[PDB]
Amino acid sequence: SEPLYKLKAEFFKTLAHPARIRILELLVERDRSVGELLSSDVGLESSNLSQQLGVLRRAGVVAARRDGNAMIYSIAAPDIAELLAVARKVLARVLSDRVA
Amino acid sequence: EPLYKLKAEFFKTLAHPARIRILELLVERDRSVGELDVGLNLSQQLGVLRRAGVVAYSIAAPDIAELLAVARKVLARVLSDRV
């Protein structure tokens, strides 16, 4: 279609990964460092973890900061936490009506 | 985990320029099969949104309206900062 609509589709495609969703859920809960994310239920190696975090960083969904020999990651702006909140709200309704 | 496998399929369904325009046309007003900028194969893409639970043809629930609203708000901030 249009190039603008290609960016809208590529935006949702960036979130269509199980590992990337769990990273966002942990960052919405509280600020996580690379070691805390590496020791989480995401189950990715340090190299795979940096690759997925790099995709979310260039997409403007996560932000990184150095606090002393470490990189603390967090969600960029509160609108990301609002996006995931409404996303799971819609997913909870479609799954409830699909089972019932 | 099958739970997060379903969360990815929710965003993967909406990751299509044709399906996004269908949702944007249905969130403004009820559209018919004849009225449906998409430029479409149309019965195949429209059937996926019906099975996903977002298309009734009209909008399923008002939660989809605020979903596209916060999605455009987030994306507008990203483009205003990534460019």
Image (tube, coloured by chain):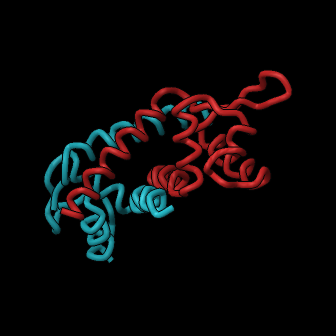
Chain colours: A red, B cyan
The answer to whether residue B75 of the structure is visible from this angle is yes
Looking at the image, residue A85 sits to the left or right of residue A98; the answer is right
* Depth check, front residue: B42 or A82: A82
Q: Is residue B17 left or right of residue B46?
A: right
Q: Residue furthest top?
A: A67
- Say if A71 sits above or below B35 in the image: above
Dividing the picture into quadrants, the one containing residue A40 is: top right
Look at 72% across and 50% down and name the residue there: A49
Q: Which of the 4 quarters of the picture holds residue B55?
A: bottom left
Q: Residue at x 62, y 29 (%)?
A: A31
Residue B83 in sight here: no
Q: Is A11 or A47 nearer to us in this picture?
A: A47
Residue B3 location (% of width, % of height): 44, 58
Q: Position of residue B34 (x, y in %)?
A: 16, 68
Q: Quadrant of the C terminus of chain B?
A: top right
Q: Position of residue A15 (x, y in %)?
A: 52, 51
Task: Please name whichever residue, A2 or B10, is drawn nearer the observer in this view of the structure.
Answer: B10
User: In the image, A24: left or right of A53?
Assistant: left
| Vertical side of B71 occupied by A91: above or below | below
Please report the residue visible at 52 percent of the width from the left and 32 percent of the height from the top.
Answer: A29
